[PDB]
Length: 13
Ligand SMILES: *C(=O)CCCCCCCCCCCN
Image (tube, rainbow, N blue to C red; front, side):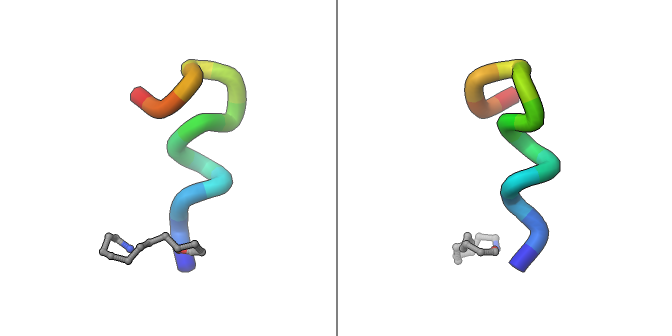
């Protein structure tokens, strides 16, 4: 619900 785009590579950022 809009999270995979939060750790797209920034390891949760
Ligand atoms: C999409 O969101 C799939 C995984 C769930 C992550 C969100 C947790 C719910 C609590 C509020 C934080 C913002 N969605």
